[PDB]
Image (tube, coloured by chain):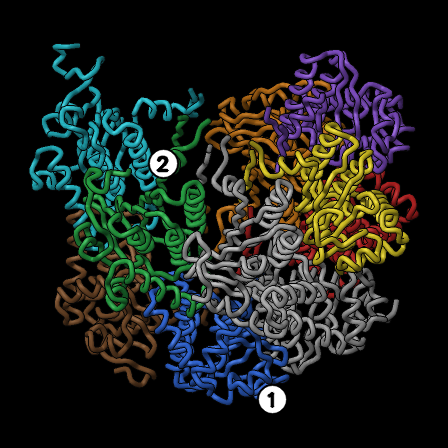
Chain colours: A yellow, D blue, E green, F brown, G red, H purple, I cyan, J orange
C-alpha cells in the first residue's frame, strides 16, 4: 500500500498539520509511541486548539492503551474522537476518552469493549506479565472505562467478558460515544 | 515502479490527488482503507465544495474496510464521481455504486460483481476476529447499503450476491450499480 | 520428541492406539481431523464392540473439522469415553460432550469453554471459503449439537457461546458438558 | 500433525489394507497421482471386491478430478463413497462418481457443486490453460456431473455458478448421493 | 538501475513522462496497469489534446490489466503513438495495435505475437482468481478488440491467438497490427 | 502422504513390483533418471515380460524426454502406455513411444504435442544451450514424433507450434495412441 | 543427538521409558505435555502398580501444560519418584513437588525456583491466548497446588512466586518442595 | 508510519528541536548510542536550558543503561524525566536519574526496578560477560539506584529480586519519582 | 554505495555528460533503463554525440536486440568504449557504435560467444519456441556480420567458440576501431602517446 | 553422515561398549542426551566402567553442572579422555573422572576459562539474575578446586585467564592424570611405549 504525498510530506503529516491524528491499526507499543509523539507535538504547537483523532483499530495491548489514554488526559485542549470502521478493545477505550460531547461514530461503525486474548502488555507478542500486574492493569482498564462511559465497574467487567459489537446507537446508549454523524464534524 | 511529477516533487498518485483524484486499484484491505480515508479527509479539508473523482480497479476486499470507506464517502458534503476501470468486485462494486447518482461511470469493457469471490469471511485478516452475530450484522449492513445504492431489494441483493458472475457496463446500468458508460473525457451516453 | 515402544516398533501414540486410545492434544484442524477420523475408522474395523477412549487437550479448532470428527464419533457403534485433560475449548468441548452419556470425564483442574476464543471464522484456513448462508448453517449445526449433547436449549447455548470464559469440572458437570470428575484410574465420584 | 502407525505401516496404509482410500485434502496433481496409485494397487490385489473412498475435500483442480474420475470408472468393482465433513468442487464430483446406491453422506456433511476460482488445472498454482481447453474441461465436468446426478447440463452449469452448500438431504434430492447414514456402512 | 535528471529532480521515467512518453517494458500486471493508467490520466489532465508516446517492450500480461489500459487509451481524446521495441506479445501486442491508425511503429528487429505464451488463465490476482465464464468472456473481448484494431476477422484472430509464433515488422504491417517500420524517426514529424 | 503396502515399501514400489511405472509429474532430469532406473531394473528382473507406464505429465524437457525415450526403445519387452489425465509435450512423446497397439488413453484424457513454454533444454529452469543444439534437439523430437504418430515431420512442426489439446478419439486418429479404454478388460 | 539401543531398536529415551523412566528436560510446552501424558498413560496401561521415575531439568513452562501433567500424575495409582537434576523452575518445581512424599530427590548442585521467570502469561497457544480471568484462575490453582505439595500456606506461596531467586537442595528440603538430597542412589532401595 | 513536520523532519526530530528526547523501547546498545547522540547535541546547542526525556521502556541492558546514565549526569543542564506508560529495569534507572524535583509520572504509570529476565550485559541477546564483571555492573546499578531513590543498597537488591510494579504514589514514596502529573501545568 | 554530486548520483552526472554506463548482464530491466537513457539523450539534443561505456559479461538476445535497435534509431554518433570485458550482447552493443568511434582499453576482453546457457531471454520464465530461436540467432548473426564486416558464416562459426580476444584482435576482427591508452582517441601504435 | 553398524549408528555401538561421546558445545539438549546415556549405562550395569570421550569447545554452567552431578551420581568408575580440546565445561567434565583414569591425547588442549560470553545457560533466552550468577560460579569454582586439587582462589584467578594448557600442563594442574600416546593407559614418559 503506497502512501501519497502533499505539497513535501506524506498524507498523515498533512492531516497532522490540520491537528488530525489517525489511529487505524492495532494498538502496539511503537504505535503508542508515535501517537504520544504526535500528541506532544500538537500540544507544543498550540495547547488550546482542539485535536481530532480518527480511530479504526481492531484492538491492542492494555499497556499501550493506558499510555495513550494518560497522554490524552494530560492535554489541556479538547479531543474530538471519531470511530470510523471499528473500535475494539483499546480502540474503544481511546474513543470514550475524548472530551464529553465530542465523541462521534459513523453510521455503520462497530464498537466492542471485549479484550483480545493476548491484549495484556504486548512488549513482544503479549508475554511479559505476572499475576498482581494482570489484576492491576485490568482494574485500571475497568475503572477508566467505567469513568468514561458512566457504567459501573461491574457492568464494564461483565461486558468486557462478552464478545459482541455495538452499533453507533447502542454505543450512545452505553455511554461510549455522544453522537452519530453522517456529515462533517459537529454537523 | 513509482513515477514522479514536479510541475515540488511528488509521485503520480499525489499529483492526481492534487487534482482531487483518488485511486483504488488493489484489494480493499485495512491499510488500503486507512490511506483512502486519509486522502478523502484531506480532500475535504482542502475544499469541501469541489467534486472528488475515485477510480476503482479493485479485485475485492473486506467489508470492515469497505464499510469504513463507504461511511467516509457518505461523510463528505461534496459530489463523488466513481469510475470503474477494469474490474469492480465485492467492496469495489460497493464503493462504485456509492458515488452520487448520475456520476457513477464505467469504461466499456469493465466488469462488475457484487459477489465476494472467495473467503466470504471479511474482517481484519492480520488477526481475523469475527463471529455469528457479527457476521450477520456486517453482511446485513452490506446488503442494505447495496440495496439503497442500486435500488434493488435486499432479497434480490442477497440472492444475487450468492452467485459468482460478472456484469458488463450495460448490465451494471440496468442493475443500478452505475449510471453511464464513458468512451471519452466528455461524459458519453449511457446504456451502450 | 517422539518416544517409541516395542512391547514391532511404533511411537507412543500408536501404542495407545493399540489400546484403543485416541489423542487429540492440539488445535482441531483439517489434517488433525483427518488423522483422527482415520484412527476412529481403524478402531471400528478392528473391533466394533470394545470401547474407545479419547483424551482431549485442545485449544480450539474449526467447526468443519470438529463436525467431521463429531459425525465420525456418532458413526461408531461402540461406546466412546471422552476425557478432558488440561483444556477443552470450542471444538474440544464439542467432542468432549459428544462422548456417550456417563462416560465423559474431566481431570480436577481441567478448564472447558464453549466459546471460540477468537477468529470465530471457522473453515479450512489454507483457503478459507465461507459465506453468510454457510456461516449461519455451520453455527446452527454447532449450536444444535451442543444443545443435544449438554441438555441446554439452543438459545442458552448461543448466548453462552458469545461469552469468553472457562468452566471448571464441577461447572462443566452442571452445564451438561461432562458427567464425572476422575482422580484415579477407577472412575472417581462426580461433582467434586 | 503426527501420523500414527499400526502393527509396521501408517494408519492410511492399514486402512488401504482394508481397501479404504482417504481423500481429505484439496484435489491437486500429486494427490491425484497418489489416489490413482492406490486405486490401481487395489485393482491388482483383487479387482472384484468393493473399495471405500472417504472424502473431506474443500475443492481442487478439474484436471486432477477428471484423472481420478476416469480411474474410478476404469475399475470393474463397486466404489462406495462417503462424504465426511465437506465435499466441494472435485470432492463432490468424486462423491457422485461412486456406484449408484453406494454414495453416502454423514448427517452434518456439506456438499457444493461450485468451483473454486483457480480450479481449472493447477499444474502449478492454477495457471497453464487456453480458451478452447477451458471450454472443453468445463464441458467435461458439466457432462460428468449431469450424468452422475441425473440433472441436466443446464441445471449443473447454473448451480455450479452459485456459491452455496447442500445438506445431506438436499444432496439426496439433487442426485449427488443416495443415503444418509448415522451408522456403519449400509446401516 | 534508477538514473536521475535534475533539469528539484526526478528519475529517468518521470523525465520521459515530462516529455509525454510512457514506458511499458515489463509483464502487464495489475500494479503495472494501475501506474500506466495513472500516467495516462495525468497526461490527459495536463493537456488532453497533445499526443502521447507509448513505448512497448512487454513479454505478455493479463487480460484484465491489458483491457484496463486499452479502455484508458480509448478514453483519451488525443492521438496515441505506439512503438514496439524488442517484443510485443499477448497484451503487449494489444496495446501496440491500440494506437491511433498511422501512428503504430515497430523497430526493424521487433517481434510481435498475439498468442499468450505459457497458458493464459488471466487473473485479477497475480495467481489468478477467475471462473470459467469470466475467462471465456474476457477472451471473447480480447478477440473482438484485436479484430477491430487489426482489421482481421474474429475467426482469424482466434485461430492466430492459438498459434505460438512471432511476426517480424513486415508481417505485422501486413497483419494490421502496426502501420510503419522506422529505423530513425522517419515518419510523422519525428515526435519522439 | 505416501501410503505403504505389506516386505515393506511405498505404493509406487508395489506397483513397480507389478511392473508398473508411474510418470505423473513434469519430465525433469531427476525424474528421467528415476524412470530410467526403474526401466533398467524391470529389464534385469525379466526382459521378456511387459511393462506398464501410466503417464500424467504436464510437460517436461527435451533432454529428459529423449533419455527416457531411448531407454524405452532400448528395452526388448513390450511397453504398454496409458494416458490418465493429461499428456503434454514430452508426456505425449512417451505416450506415443509405447509399442504400437499397446497405447491407451482414458475417456476424458487430453493430449498435446505442443510444449506450452520455454522449449528449452531445461537442465533445471536455467538453460545450457546453443543454436545448433536447440535445432538438433528439436529435429530429433520432430523425427521421433513423426515416426511414432505417422504424421509428416512438417505436420508435427506445425502442430507443435499450436497450443491445443486433443481428445482420445482425435489422438487415435492422429496416431498418438491406439485405443480409448473405459475398463481394464479392453487391454490386450 | 539421538542415540539408539538394540537390546528391533528404539532411541535412548524409549529405552529409559522401558525402564519406567520419563524425562522432562526442556520447557514445559503443550506438545511436551502431551508426550509426557502419553508416556504416563502408557506406563499405567502396562502396569498401574509399579513405580515411575520422572527426571526433571526444566527451566519453566506454561501453567496449562504443567497442570495437565500434574493432574495426570495425580491420576496414577502408583508411586511417582521425582528427581531434580540441574534446575527445576516454575512448572518444573511444580512437577518436582508432585511426586509421592518421601520420593522427591534433588542432586547436590540442583537449583529450584517456584517463581516463573521472564513474566508468566501462561498460554494455551505458544504465543498465549488467554483472558485475564483465566490467567488469574490458573495462577490461583498453581498457588493452591504448590501449597498442598510443599505444606506452606497459599500466602507464602504467592509471596515466594513473586520472588526471582533459586533455592539449593537444602533450602528446598526445608521448604517442603523435596524430601532428600542424593549423591549416589542413597535412599529407598536405589530404584533408578 | 513515522509522521513529518514542516525544514522537513520526522516527529521525533521536531520534538528534539523542542529539546525533547523519546525513549520508548528496550534500552539496547544502538538505542543508547542514539540517545547519547541526542543528549550531546542538546548540550552543544544550549548547555543551560532544560531537556525533557519521556520514558516508556520495558527494560534494557545494564551497559546501555549505564552509558545513558553517565551521559545524563554528564550534562550541566536540568533533566526532566517523565514516565509515560511503563518504566522497568533500566527504564526506571533513567527515570530516577533526572534532576530531583523534575521526575514525573503519569497517573496510570507502572514502574519496576526488577529486570524481568536474563540480567545479562546483553550486547545483543548473546552475552559477553564474566563473574567479576557481572558483579561489578550489578554493584554499580545498585549503588546508582540507592543514590537516586534514597533507599539502602540492601533494599535495592532485595526489591530488584522481586518481580512487581509500583504505582505513581508508591513510586513517589520510594524515591523513584517526585510527583504524578495529570496536566502539563503541574510541571515546574 | 553509489556517490552523489543540484543533487544527482554519479551515473546521473555522467548522463548529463551524455555518458551511458552498461556494467551488468544485459537483462530485460537493464535494457529498459538503457533505452530510457538513450531516448532521453535523444530528446535533449539529437545531434550531439553519446558515450556508452560497456563492461558487460553477457546477456539475453531480446534485451540486446532492443538496445541495438534503439542505438541505430538515434541520429547522433555513438562512441562505444569497452572497459573490462564485453561478451555476447556486450560485444554486440560495442560493435554497434559509429564506425571509427569504437574503442577498447588496452587490457579489455571481447567475446562474441554466449557463454553458459544462452537463449533469447525473458529472465526466470524463459519463453522460447523452435522458430524463435532460429529467428533471434539469425538476427544476432546478421547484425554482428554487418557491424564487424565478417561474413555471417564466419560469425556463426566463431560464436560457437568460447574464447576471448584482446583489443588488437578485436580491431582485426572488426569488433572495434581503436585502442585508447593513457589518452583520448589514440590507438595502440603509441605514435601519439 | 553418521555411519551404521542388528542395526545401530556408530554412537549407539560405542554406547554398547559403554562409551559416551561429548563432541559439541555443552548445551541443554546435549546435557539431556548425555544424562540419558549415563542413566541407561547405570541401569544396564552399575559396576562396570564407563568411557567418556570429550572434544568440547565450551558450554553453559547449568548443563555442565547437571552432567557433573549425574557423573558423581554413578557408582561405577568413569574414565574420561580429552581428544582435541576440552574448554570450560569440557575441562570440568574431564576433571570429573575417577582419580587415575583421566587421560588426554598428546596434542590435546585444555582451558578452564569460559571463552566469549559466559553465563549460566538456557540458550537463546538467557534467564540469569544477580544472586544466581554468583551461586553457579561458586559451584563451578568449588567443583574445579575439588577435582583438580587447586585452591578455589587459584581456580577463580586462572579461570579469569584466556589460555590453553597442553597435556603435561594439565597433569601438573590436576586436571588430568596421564597422557596416553600410541597405546593404552601409558603416560608420556614413554618408558612403556
Q: Residue at x 27, y 45 (%)?
A: E83
Q: Residue at x 85, y 44 (%)?
A: A140
Give the Cα separation between the discs numbered 2 and 1: 79 Å
Give the residue at mark 2: E19
Left or right of H142 in this view: I166: left
Left or right of F161 in this view: J31: right
Dot label at residue F108: none
Q: Tell me the element at label 1.
A: loop
Q: Residues within 10 Å of mark 1 (few under 14, many from 20)?
A: few
Quarter holding the C terminus of chain E?
top left
Q: Is the same chain shared between marks 2 and 1? A: no
Residue G94 horizontal/vertical position (percent): 79, 49
Q: Nearer the viewer, residue H57 or A79?
A: A79
Q: Nearer the viewer, residue E147 or F179?
A: E147
Q: Residue at x 40, y 72 (%)?
A: D37
Q: Nearer the viewer, residue G135 or E63?
A: E63
Left or right of I106 in this view: E3: right
Badge nearest the viewer, 2 or 1: 2
Q: Are marks 2 and 1 in contact (CB under 8 Å)?
A: no
Dot label at residue D187: 1
Q: Nearer the viewer, residue D139 or G32?
A: D139
Q: Residue D124: which quarter of the image?
A: bottom left
Q: Residues within 10 Å of mark 2 (few under 14, many from 20)?
A: some
In the rendered view, tell whether residue E107 sits above or below residue J117.
below
In the rendered view, tell whether residue D62 sits above or below residue G21.
below
Residue I56 horizontal/vertical position (percent): 27, 32
The chain holding disc 2 is E
The chain holding disc 1 is D
In the rendered view, tell whether residue J109 sits above or below residue J97.
above
Amino acid at each position: 500500500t503506497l502512501v501519497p504525498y502533499v505539497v513535501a510530506m506524506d498524507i498523515y503529516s498533512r492531516l497532522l498539520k490540520d491537528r488530525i491524528v489517525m489511529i487505524g491499526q492495532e494498538i502496539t507499543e511503537p504505535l503508542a509511541n508515535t501517537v504520544i509523539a504526535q500528541l506532544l507535538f500538537l500540544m507544543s504547537e498550540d495547547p488550546t486548539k482542539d485535536i481530532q483523532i480518527f480511530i479504526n483499530s481492531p484492538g491492542g495491548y492494555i499497556t499501550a492503551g493506558l499510555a495513550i489514554y494518560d497522554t490524552i488526559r494530560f492535554l489541556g485542549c479538547d479531543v474530538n474522537t471519531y470511530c470510523i470502521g471499528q473500535a475494539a478493545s483499546m480502540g474503544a477505550l481511546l474513543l470514550s476518552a475524548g472530551t464529553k460531547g465530542k465523541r462521534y461514530a459513523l453510521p455503520h461503525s462497530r464498537m466492542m469493549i471485549h479484550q483480545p486474548s493476548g491484549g495484556i502488555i504486548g512488549t513482544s507478542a503479549d508475554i511479559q506479565l505476572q499475576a498482581a500486574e494482570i489484576l492491576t492493569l485490568k482494574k485500571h482498564l475497568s475503572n477508566i472505562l467505567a469513568e468514561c462511559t458512566g457504567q459501573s465497574v461491574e457492568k464494564i467487567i461483565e461486558d468486557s467478558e462478552r464478545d459482541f459489537f455495538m452499533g453507533a446507537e447502542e454505543a450512545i446508549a452505553y455511554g461510549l460515544i455522544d453522537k452519530v454523524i453522517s456529515s462533517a464534524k459537529e454537523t
